[PDB]
Amino acid sequence: GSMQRASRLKRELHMLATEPPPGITCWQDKDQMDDLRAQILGGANTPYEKGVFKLEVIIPERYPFEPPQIRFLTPIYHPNIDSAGRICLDVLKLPPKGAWRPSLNIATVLTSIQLLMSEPNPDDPLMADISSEFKYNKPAFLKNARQWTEKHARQK
């Protein structure tokens, strides 16, 4: 990619290293500024509480004009996230349907995903059956979401 992309990534890795949003961390997997990983802590008072969720964060060649490409590596039980970790979230897509713009950044999208974990959009699901459970049988949703968290997001 370009020098301007390189330069922007150096600045974002700096901010992600020194002022990460609460509950989030993001780092270079090895020596490439565009092959990143992240971690989001399950939020308190959510079924994901105490889980630790890892994600792959790939920065496309045309960043920042295309959004980061992000998927969960740790399985998670959620209306908007599929069994391969694909995430349905507006800021991960370009307009007109999406909301990605170059004034957003790696940190703000990881924060949007963290918020999506607390506040699902059952209206625009990737997982139709989880989405129905969330809407109509919340207690069963919360229970299944805790159990998936215990099974996959707690090595302890």
Image (tube, rainbow, N blue to C red):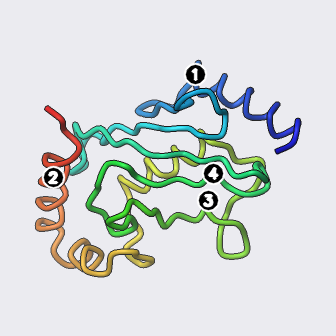
Label 3 or label 2, whichever comes before in sequence order: 3
Residue depth check, mark 1 versus mark 2: number of the one nearer the observer? 1
Q: Amino acid at mark 1?
A: Ala
Residue at numbered disc 1: 17
The quarter of the picture where residue 99 lies is: bottom right
Q: Are marks 1 and 3 in contact (CB under 8 Å)?
A: no
Q: Secondary structure at mark 2?
A: helix
Residue under pointer 4 = 68
C-alpha separation, residue under disc 1 versus residue under disc 4: 17 Å
Find the residue positioned furthest to the front.
Answer: 31
Residue type for callout 3: Val
Earlier sequence position, callout 1 versus callout 4: 1
The quarter of the image holding the C terminus is: top left
Tell us which disc is closer to us: 4 or 2: 4
Circle 2 packing at 10 Å, graded few (<14), some (14-19), many (20+), is: many
User: At x 66% / y 75%, what residue is drawn?
Assistant: 97
* Vertical order, 69 against 25 (above or below): below
Near mark 4 (Cα within 10 A), the count class, few <14, some 14-19 or many ≥20, is: many
- In the image, residue 59 lies at what x, y percent? 66, 47
What amino acid is labelled 2 in the image?
A: Arg
Label 3 belongs to which residue? 91
Depth order, front residue of 118/64: 64
At which x and y percent is residue 110? Answer: 52, 45
Question: As displayed, is residue 11 above or below residue 114?
Answer: above
Q: Which residue is mark 2?
A: 146
Give the position of the N terminus as an image quadrant: top right
Relative horizontal placement of residue 100, taking residue 54 as reference (left or right): right
Q: How many residues crowd mark 1 within 10 Å: few (<14), some (14–19), many (20+)?
A: few
> Spatial distance from mark 3 to mark 4, Cα to Cα?
9 Å
